[PDB]
Image (cartoon, rainbow, N blue to C red):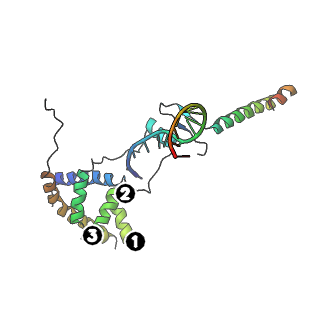
RNA sequence: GAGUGGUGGAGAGGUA
């Protein structure tokens, strides 16, 4: 199949992308004042995941919008896996409840197929971009 | 959460008035409790009442 | 389970 360093590269990139698109919904955990100051004084297991500067996120959202218009179910499972944090066991049970092992099999192979379609267009979309240079002074 | 406690920008905590009022009545209720189980003189316990 | 604080309250001045 795909080599594993490309696999962890897409894992980190779509993890960062799902963490970016998860910070935009309205029905979300709003904290009080006291929990906010307890978190700023001594945190526990409340840590977050990195996001983008939203232009890289814009271009990768544009490429997944262009190629993933023909498949609704793969888009839905990559959203519910990358934004919420549900496991493939969990989304397999969630899709079987409304067998289950073949359901887990079909969701992982449609994830593999969607990743195989999104990878090389993502490499071309990465390499054909001009990096904006730092600020200079003319005398 | 209807007599809330958000601090100021420099870490100093600025409350509502109700927390102060409840602090006063709770502290004097504790002192009246101490004087009733201490069995204080009647002038002292009626002054705290 | 994935960023964040003024409203609170006072005083002073201003607009329609």
Left or right of residue B10, residue B38 in this image = right
Decide which of tag 3 and tag 1 comes sooner along the chain.
1
B43 or B41: nearer the eye? B43
Q: Quadrant of the C terminus of chain A?
A: top left
Determine whether the residue tagged by mark 3 lies in a helix, strand or loop.
helix
The residue carrying mark 2 is A84
| Quadrant position of the N terminus of chain A in the picture | bottom left
How far, Cα to Cα, is label 3 from label 2?
Answer: 20 Å
Residue C6 position, x and y percent, is 50, 39
Q: Is residue A133 above or below residue A11?
A: above
Q: In the picture provided, is A39 more to the left or to the right than A57?
A: right
Quadrant of the image occupied by residue B22: top right
Q: Which residue matches tag 3? A: A106
- Could you tell me how far apart the alpha carbons at marks 3 and 1 are, in whole angstroms? 15 Å
Q: Are marks 2 and 1 on the same chain?
A: yes
Nearer the observer, A52 or B10: B10
Going by the image, does A59 lie left or right of B8? left
Q: Quadrant of residue A124?
A: bottom left
Can residue A127 be spotted in the picture? yes
Name the one closer to the observer, A34 or A25: A25
Disc 2 from disc 1: Cα separation: 19 Å
Cβ atoms under marks 3 and 1 closer than 8 Å: no
- Which one is earlier in the sequence, the residue at label 3 or at label 2? 2
Answer with mark 2 or mark 1, whichever residue precedes in sequence. Answer: 2
- Residue furthest bottom as drawn: A99
Residue at image point 21% right, 52% down = A8
* Circle 2 chain: A
Badge 2 marks a residue whose secondary structure is: helix
């Amino acid at each position: 199949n795909l080599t594993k360093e490309q696999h962890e590269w897409l894992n980190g990139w779509l993890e960062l992308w799902g963490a970016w698109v998860y910070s935009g919904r309205l029905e979300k955990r709003m904290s009080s004042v006291i929990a906010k100051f307890m978190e700023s004084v001594e945190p526990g297991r409340v840590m977050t995941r990195p996001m983008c500067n939203d232009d890289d996120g814009m271009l990768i959202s544009q490429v997944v919008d262009s190629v993933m218009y023909i498949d609704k179910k793969a888009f839905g499972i990559l959203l519910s896996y990358y934004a919420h944090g549900s496991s493939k066991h969990a989304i397999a049970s969630y899709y079987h409840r409304v067998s289950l092992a073949t359901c887990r099999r079909e969701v992982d192979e449609i994830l593999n197929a969607s990743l195989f379609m999104i990878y090389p267009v993502l490499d071309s979309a990465f390499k054909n971009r001009k990096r904006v240079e730092k600020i200079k002074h003319v005398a | 959460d209807l007599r809330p406690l958000v601090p100021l920008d420099g870490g100093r905590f600025a409350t509502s008035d109700l927390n102060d009022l409840y602090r006063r009545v709770i502290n004097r209720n504790n002192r009246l409790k101490r004087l009733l189980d201490l069995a204080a003189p009647d002038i002292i316990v009626r002054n705290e009442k």
